[PDB]
Image (tube, rainbow, N blue to C red):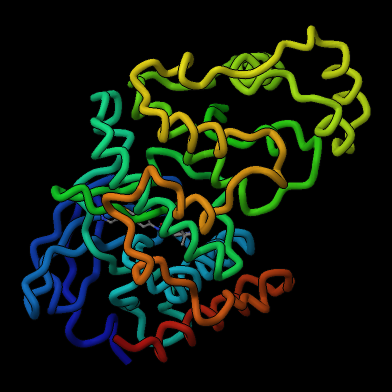
Length: 336
Ligand SMILES: Cn1nc(C(C)(C)C)cc1NC(=O)Nc1ccc(Sc2ccncc2)cc1
């Protein structure tokens, strides 16, 4: 019967209190977020710099407890060099009544792609970063998990341009079939995002903006060209079928004319990732084989997940307290 488990100290971090185990020292505020806060730390065991996320009131609502539970499960399931993973998870609580929040420990990443964007990267850097992106996407897709919100702010990089995929209205990087829901989407939605990111790296300029869904669609069709019947039939929205069939049928493309600084292989890969047809758009596994990644491709590194991510409670409707017992029990039996 304690106030917190022995080995935990209290310390204010960016105007708020934190309870950490002994082994983590030198907490330094990194950022505030929608559902928690993040600081940096030093594991006095190994000596590595880690990142710790305190969840802010995860048990305030069924939606929030389900959210935090899912994030812990995802971080626990993914074991890939280009996907952020779990090092430790702990709570200062001693029973279920003191259980108010928990902390996640992750490898520390210096920055992300949104903060260093616009510097018109060389073809080499685009090759390396995009190749890592597609490896992480192949892995998470192989686990049955789709990101749905990939963007430069969700691509962390360190000093060596080593990349990991993260997660936590501007919709510049979302696939058209998602913004318009004009056909049912598959995993290749993430692939569209990669294209939008890669093009930005080539140009230093965001590809599709738009102040509403229709304007962004017009900007997109400026690049993809108005699609032909072969595609228009696959749409399930009839009003969008009519709108597309009513547009001035403006043909594609010419991606080597859209990005004059783009190499033919880069322009080609960009052609195949920015494809309106969700059945013709490259998968991550297919995009890894493109000749644009020849100087870096190592198929042994293009791993899949052993097991699909199995959130059996993904649909369940439990009280906040039941979710609490689930998360708590998940914390204790976690093991490094
Ligand atoms: C929900 N979800 N889904 C995924 C995928 C990519 C496997 C699909 C990952 C997460 N959670 C998460 O990214 N949490 C998180 C992100 C950023 C920080 S801040 C930070 C992290 C590492 N180094 C420095 C700062 C903290 C936690």
